[PDB]
Image (spheres, coloured by chain):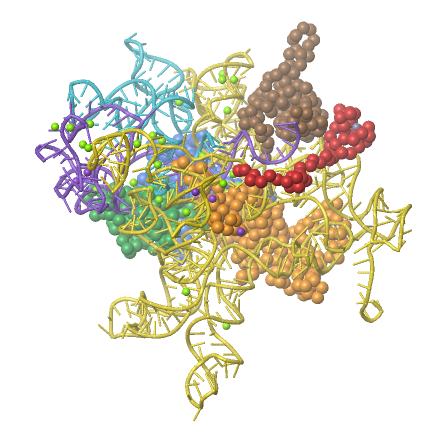
Chain colours: A red, B blue, C brown, D green, E orange, F cyan, G purple, H yellow
Amino acid sequence: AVPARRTSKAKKAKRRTHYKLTIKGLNACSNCGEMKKSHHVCPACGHYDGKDV
Amino acid sequence: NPLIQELTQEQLRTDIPAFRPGDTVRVHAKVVEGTRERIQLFEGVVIKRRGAGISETYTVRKVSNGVGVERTFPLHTPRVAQIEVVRYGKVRRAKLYYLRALHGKAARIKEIRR
Amino acid sequence: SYRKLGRTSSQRKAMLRDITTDLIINERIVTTEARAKEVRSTVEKMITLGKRGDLHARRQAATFVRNEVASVREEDESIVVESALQKLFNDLGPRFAERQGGYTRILKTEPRRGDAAPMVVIEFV
Amino acid sequence: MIQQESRLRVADNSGAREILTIKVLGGSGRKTANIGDVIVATVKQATPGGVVKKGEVVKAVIVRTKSGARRADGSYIKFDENAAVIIRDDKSPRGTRIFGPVARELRENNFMKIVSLAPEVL
Amino acid sequence: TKGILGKKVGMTQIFTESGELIPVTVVEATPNVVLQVKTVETDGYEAIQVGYQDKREVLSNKPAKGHVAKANTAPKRFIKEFKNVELGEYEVGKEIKVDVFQAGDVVDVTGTTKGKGFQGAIKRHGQSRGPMSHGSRYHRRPGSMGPVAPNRVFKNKRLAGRMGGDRVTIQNLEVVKVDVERNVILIKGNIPGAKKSLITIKSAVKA
RNA sequence: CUCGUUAAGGAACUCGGCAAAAUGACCCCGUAACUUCGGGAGAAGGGGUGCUGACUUCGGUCAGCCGCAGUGAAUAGGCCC
RNA sequence: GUAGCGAAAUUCCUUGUCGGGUAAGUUCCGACCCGCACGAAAGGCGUAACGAUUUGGGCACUGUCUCAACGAGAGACUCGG
RNA sequence: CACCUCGAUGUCGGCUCGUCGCAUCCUGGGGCUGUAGUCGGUCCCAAGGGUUGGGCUGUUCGCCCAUUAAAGCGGCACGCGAGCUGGGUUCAGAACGUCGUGAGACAGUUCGGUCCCUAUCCGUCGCGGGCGUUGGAAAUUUGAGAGGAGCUGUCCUUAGUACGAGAGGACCGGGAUGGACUUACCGCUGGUGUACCAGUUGUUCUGCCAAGGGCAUUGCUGGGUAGCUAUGUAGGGAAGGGAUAAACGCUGAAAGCAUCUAAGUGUGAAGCCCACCUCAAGAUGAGAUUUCCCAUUUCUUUAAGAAAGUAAGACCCCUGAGAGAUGAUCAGGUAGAUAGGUUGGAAGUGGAAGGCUAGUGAUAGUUGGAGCGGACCAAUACUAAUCGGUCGAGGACUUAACC
Ligand SMILES: [K+]
Ligand SMILES: [K+]
Ligand SMILES: [K+]
Ligand SMILES: [K+]
Ligand SMILES: [K+]
Ligand SMILES: [Mg+2]
Ligand SMILES: [Mg+2]
Ligand SMILES: [Mg+2]
Ligand SMILES: [Mg+2]
Ligand SMILES: [Mg+2]
Ligand SMILES: [Mg+2]
Ligand SMILES: [Mg+2]
Ligand SMILES: [Mg+2]
Ligand SMILES: [Mg+2]
Ligand SMILES: [Mg+2]
Ligand SMILES: [Mg+2]
Ligand SMILES: [Mg+2]
Ligand SMILES: [Mg+2]
Ligand SMILES: [Mg+2]
Ligand SMILES: [Mg+2]
Ligand SMILES: [Mg+2]
Ligand SMILES: [Mg+2]
Ligand SMILES: [Mg+2]
Ligand SMILES: [Mg+2]
Ligand SMILES: [Mg+2]
Ligand SMILES: [Mg+2]
Ligand SMILES: [Mg+2]
Ligand SMILES: [Mg+2]
Ligand SMILES: [Mg+2]
Ligand SMILES: [Mg+2]
Ligand SMILES: [Mg+2]
Ligand SMILES: [Mg+2]
Ligand SMILES: [Mg+2]
Ligand SMILES: [Zn+2]
């Protein structure tokens, strides 16, 4: 079907509320201190649970 | 399921022989009228056993008067007093559902003596 | 239940066989999440056969493995050509004779660029 | 699971040989029948020198079915054909001799003459 | 009245003083515990709060341990109230064994149904499929939404959505056997719920 | 949407058997009314088909074996009034 | 307006009447002929074979349907472009 | 009548979904009867639910068959084509009859003939996030209010009693069992079961035999686990109240009588409010109870002040299913059986490979209800749930017994 009416800037921006993305799981690596996703290998040092990989 | 087996162990039954599909068996099936209780012998070949423990059922096929009949019983009933195996037929199957389409000389099971 | 991986039955079977063979060869592999979570059980059920060692198990594993070439552990010229089957039954069963399971571990890694595919490293031991 | 336009064999000597269910009796929207359920039917094939003949509309009783019957004790009967017996307004039959076997479920529904005339009652 | 609450186990197939089968559902009723007693003069109504399944303390929390500590028991998982019962018979800390029931008595059974997910109107409400041949392009759909004149759709027009998760009673069932050694009830017939799901057993309201 | 199975029933669906299903190869037997005597006709309807040894005078044949099933899968008429 | 055909690809009245087929048949087949408004090279009557022709009946076959159920795959769905 | 619609108006019937009215088809109540009883006729009340399947026709209707307790009448754009069909509608072709000098037409008929749209808003069905509910949190809950369900036959008994000359044949009451409809569920019957098992054809591959892999609709065929499931299983609409409709009144006066009414009072329906089930405190009117954390630091200020670390607790993240479109819900995160694997089993398949014996060989038998074994069960920390982080209170004022 067809819109029949242009939406407003307001109604756009009110749809766009939950379109935002979140980034999560960041903690610090106990070895190098730089931040890594939890449960993920530190891409810099490669260590995970204190073991090189 | 462990609890299930523990509960149903007492109503399980032990007069049963270790019969199979393919083998001919007579069932001493007792029927109840409320005023009388009559045993009648239903003989037939076993097309299937299926189930586990107390959910085990088996079917028995017969050809009375040109009409193929097929009678399922639970294995562990008090209303089946005896299950007499009378031939040990040989088949390469467990479910003999091909017997429903056949009649007579083709529906014959090859006895083993064992 | 079990996963499907966007492939048909035959296609996923072939992909699992290829990945497991490659994994037995390389002792370490990069994959995605789901592929790894299935290849886990797969390779472990193959190494069970490796530990059992009988010819029955040998054939149950040849049913699955692709007959790739794991390594030319040569001594003189070209003699010792070794297949993945031979590797499974003469390097890895003897390796995990003592473990009661747990022949792999999974390590989550950087997501892939072109897809945001979550990537994973499987490794023996 | 016997329905309208469902064809049946005849299990008596009334004269009919094949039957077609017009309707099932009992209630308003009963779309299904089994043993002990009365039927209204035609006669699509009759014995030549028979009382009941081609085209006749007549009541009937289902006596054996593939989709068979069930007992309280889990014992189930099934058959390799769907057959019926022609009756009058009374539960008595038109013919005199029933063929093949018959289910026990009819004794509760008071088709006792058919149960008696049948050779084997399972 | 009375009642307990317990855990669904599964289905069985049982013979009852005769060859007559009875299909059966198994309810494991590890002895429920009274936790609180509510009255009109403090709470607005007569009732009794009950717990069934022990948690691990790491899974529980402080304000729940504090609520259990009066009865002097362990952190319970499922907690429910029973209404329209005698309060002089029941006390805090009382354990409600399965002996409370008698095999044969009539009973009512509440449970939360198996989640079927986002389902269509046909499976969710028994609506009929359209024809599948004769040029039909209308197969699995719910039909018209209503007339034209309202310029709107009336409510309780039945459509696709989540099937399952609802709370459902089954009335006029019957208790087949009790095992207090095992803390088990056998109930004639099917009852709502997945396995390892909570059930509330109560004496019948109708009876 | 494109496919695959289905209890019992079996066109009760429907404008209407639409669509799908079923038949489908080869060998042999057998084949109506009607007919412009050419046809109808691959009418219809049936049966057989795998493997292993003997046997032919090289295709028939006999015996045995296995399977629910032998053009074992794919490809091949639904028919009649 | 002859032969011949006739409720017809033609008949309104008309679901004509009768018979057959069906449990039930405004359709169909066969006869009747009050041919509203057949008719002889705008050809009439008949006709084997032929027809992705139109129509009706039957057997087999089946998810067409009773009354839906399950599975597979593409899309839909979440993420990235 | 031509007021709206010709810069679109889609035309009948059927299908899916229904909703409403009552001038009620059945069930329910009652009065009158030319109501003996059974059947009934008629009228008043009553719209809670139900109100069939087929043959013919494109058909609505209608006829017929056969049932039904009953086979209601109408409206909702003769309900519903951005939901379906497109049989019927003279779109274009062709033909019969008839008309026309004719091109063509129907006062008629016949065969065939493209039904476009990714849903913006409201609306509806479901699921979330945020905030609020005046300190923060975890649970259980009253329930305003809403919805759902509401049906009914047959048989037995009372009793061959009452009725009636007979024939035939009961109210009231108590039981039995069904129909359709519906809630749930899979232990039974069966279905499906595309990472289970076995058989089997062709070709090709693992060098060859043997054993196996691939492709051929999952190659085909025979079974079948979990899960999903109906045709299968269990249950349901039970009794009962309160007030009433129509009707029946009791007492009773206006009107010395009479009278159901005017006051007073009572029987009284499948209907109404309850009772049965479900949702429900966003019920901003935001409720109630139990339990837990506590009343810290600085700065600004008499500020219901600001930030800045925390308690109770929750979340992120991860393993997952009893859940599930994604969110969510639920179970768990080494204070461990959450999943995988391993070991045991179970179902299911049905007698593995390698051997050996027999046999001309096909093949059979034995080792051995073997071997295989997805999701089912129980154990087992071997692997993975590491490390960790984020958010989140310190509680205003007035008046009431000291409140
Ligand atoms: K409006
Ligand atoms: K005529
Ligand atoms: K004419
Ligand atoms: K217009
Ligand atoms: K519309
Ligand atoms: Mg394939
Ligand atoms: Mg389609
Ligand atoms: Mg079928
Ligand atoms: Mg029809
Ligand atoms: Mg076709
Ligand atoms: Mg073939
Ligand atoms: Mg005619
Ligand atoms: Mg002339
Ligand atoms: Mg002419
Ligand atoms: Mg001329
Ligand atoms: Mg001509
Ligand atoms: Mg416009
Ligand atoms: Mg009225
Ligand atoms: Mg119809
Ligand atoms: Mg017909
Ligand atoms: Mg309309
Ligand atoms: Mg048309
Ligand atoms: Mg034209
Ligand atoms: Mg002219
Ligand atoms: Mg055409
Ligand atoms: Mg749409
Ligand atoms: Mg259901
Ligand atoms: Mg089941
Ligand atoms: Mg099961
Ligand atoms: Mg070979
Ligand atoms: Mg290839
Ligand atoms: Mg190829
Ligand atoms: Mg009253
Ligand atoms: Zn690091």
H247 to F76, vertically: above or below: below
Q: Position of residue A35 (x, y in %)?
A: 78, 31
Q: Residue at x 64, y 12 (%)?
A: C81
Q: Nearer the viewer, residue H43 or H81?
A: H81
Q: Report the quarter where the N terminus of chain E lies.
A: bottom right
Q: Quadrant of residue B111?
A: top left
Height in image: E196 above or below G72? below
Judge whether residue D119 can be spotted in this image: no
In front: C71, or F56?
C71
Tell me: B16 left or right of E49.
left
Residue found at x 68% / y 10%: C74
| Quarter of the figure that contains the C terminus of chain E | bottom right
Which of the 4 image quarters holds residue D112? bottom left
Q: What residue is at 68 percent from the left and 23 percent from the top?
A: C30
What residue is at 69 percent from the left and 37 percent from the top? A20
> What is the quadrant of residue H115 in the picture?
top left
Q: Position of residue H87 (x, y in %)?
A: 34, 38
Give percent across and percent down for residue E186. 56, 52
Instruction: Check the image and report above or below for E61 versus H174.
Output: above
D85 or H327: nearer the viewer: H327
